[PDB]
Amino acid sequence: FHLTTRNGEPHMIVSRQEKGKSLLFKTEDGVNMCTLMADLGELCEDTITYKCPLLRQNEPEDIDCWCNSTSTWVTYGTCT
Amino acid sequence: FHLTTRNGEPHMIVSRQEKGKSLLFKTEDGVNMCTLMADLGELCEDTITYKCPLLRQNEPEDIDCWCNSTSTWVTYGTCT
Amino acid sequence: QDVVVLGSQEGAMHTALTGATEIQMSSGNLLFTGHLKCRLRMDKLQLKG
Amino acid sequence: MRCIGMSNRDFVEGVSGGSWVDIVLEHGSCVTTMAKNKPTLDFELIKTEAKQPATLRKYCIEAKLTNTTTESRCPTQGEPSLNEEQDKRFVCKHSMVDR
């Protein structure tokens, strides 16, 4: 995935071949591990973009993306 | 994942902890690599079961599961 | 292909039956307010005492 | 006392002897019968119920789905099938999709 930013915050452009794998990227505050559980398809015009909240010792609820060290934005296409 | 069969064909019972990782299993015709891109959740009563087609040098379209050596059936729960 | 089931229809039913005569019941049996016509004979009755 | 306390109370008496006397019974009412040298009786219809009436049809109003399975064939190779399509506990649909 391509690591960029959105208003100072880290942003992940996730491609199709990353479905099912732990997303890791270094940050001043250590290594960040986001988990993507998404309709994740091929990167195209039909993108969706939203935030993966920070979750410390809390079970996830009503979400398919979350990181454990620093909240991150994520973007991926839905095409197939 | 648990490897079983469905009418002579290989069948994969995929659990939650395998989301995002390449699925490999040996077969007479060499090693088979299926790719799961699925709503993949926890194995429960709400299962869905369908086929992952064989794809030789063709880009995938309108699918979230496919193997590259031998067509395989896949099953997983959607619970969370 | 995905398949989803509608939600319970108990509600759609309830607020759909409003108007129709409600019938009481108990022990699984239905109860009504009946009407009878009878004929009786007292030739086998007598005063006690 | 029950019948005396009721507002709807009929008094019936036989105009003959050994004859039949007619009375009408209603819910919430009572009938008092009298006859020469016979005790006076009170009659009340208290319950009217149907016992084990024939069940016409059972309607499901809430359900769940499990083991959803899909099968599909390429253009030119006829209609696909699933054996569970013969199992009366399943709901199935046939369609066409781009391939």
Image (tube, coloured by chain):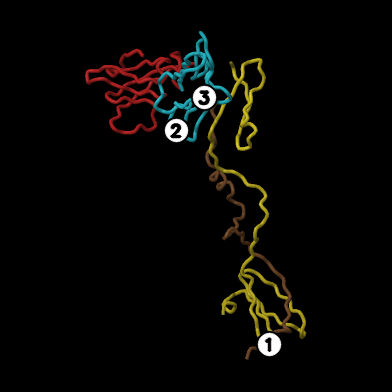
Chain colours: A red, B cyan, C brown, D yellow
Q: Nearer the viewer, residue A46 or B62?
A: B62
Residue density around tag 1, few if under 14, some if 14–19, many if 20 or more, within 10 Å:
few
**Could you tell me which residue is drawn at 44 percent across and 33 percent down?**
B79
How far apart are the alpha carbons under marks 2 and 3? Answer: 20 Å
Return the x and y of residue D97 as percentages of the image width and height: 60, 20
Instruction: Identify the residue at horizontal 58%, vertical 75% (top origin).
Output: D6
Number of callouts: 3
Q: Amino acid at mark 1?
A: Gln
Residue for badge 1? C46
Q: Chain of mark 3?
A: B
Q: Position of residue A10 (x, y in %)?
A: 30, 18
Q: Which mark is residue B11?
A: 3
The reply to whether the C-beta atoms of the residues labelled 1 and 2 are less than 8 Å apart is no
Closer to the observer: label 3 or label 1? 3
Position of residue A23 measured from the top left corner of the image (x, y, whole percent): 34, 19
Task: Give the residue type that dot 2 points to.
Answer: Cys
The chain identifier of the residue carrying mark 2 reads B
Q: Which mark is residue D87?
A: none
Q: Is residue A48 or residue D26 the one in the foreground?
A: A48
Alpha-carbon span between mark 3 and mark 1: 87 Å
Q: Secondary structure at mark 3?
A: strand
The residue at the far front in this view is B28
Mark 1 element type: loop
- Which chain is disc 1 placed on? C
Q: Is residue A78 visible?
A: no
Q: Quadrant of residue A8?
A: top left
Helix, strand or loop under label 2: strand
